[PDB]
Image (cartoon, rainbow, N blue to C red; front, side, top):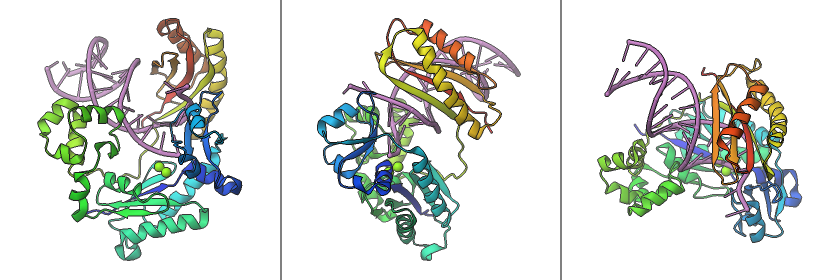
Length: 342
DNA sequence: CTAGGGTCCTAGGACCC
DNA sequence: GGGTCCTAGGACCCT
Ligand SMILES: [Mg+2]
Ligand SMILES: [Mg+2]
């Protein structure tokens, strides 16, 4: 009863797309991200920039101190979405069991596939080659018996490579695997785990489930399971979006309600346009707002509401502005909608 | 020197039984 | 006191 799971992942996705479309950017350091004047961060960088230490989520000021010649690009999201739709259609030629996790990556369940003599390794290789043909973008892949190992594997022969983990290899792989490599174990969790002497899956294997449950709740069960190769999550091809959000960080903190109100007047049309692509009648479950202060605390207040309404969002923001700001400056304003359930 | 797009989990009181 | 809704906050994911 062993499944075959592929995780396909595009290499330097946004940057790879800008390089294809402009060959002049191929061996100079580039990154998609907001300027230092806009208080931005790096979305991603190409390998010539990564050589300097440039990483996704790095503050752009830090990026430029490591890499003074970094060329900064704003991003063409329609071009990324187009490449995303194309690779998902390529995925569909092999199976319908496709769970996309973002623009540039998907799980594929090829257990019941008849392609490539049932070889998941050859399927992943054909997919990567087909993506390179047709799109001139490279992809890496991971092959494993469960989702999370397949996703760890797609990183290990990046870029333009793949890695296969058979059931026989699972125990040696896990023994030395850092817990931080499991998707969903982030910096806070890894630091708590490290401070009790837990660094690898091998360490967690020597742990009692009951202790993990008390110390981390349902997360402790996940930790215990994953540390043993256990991951029964099914590839799910019918997930649907649940929310729509539009927010902006200002170049300077704002201190007057008039400034906050002006920002909302520009955010609202964008929220309406994006909601309308998926809900023409603008009917929704909740709507709300978000402020982030200069002490980097953030607050949201949202409520049941039947249909996108600009004035109520202004009204709510006013109340949040008056009631939870406490004299701090504001660096971000956001609008938010929760979608109806079906 | 700290984005913008999201998902999922937790937790207290309201409400219902 | 157990479900379930409402709401707020936070860790985490992707580029
Ligand atoms: Mg990628
Ligand atoms: Mg990815």
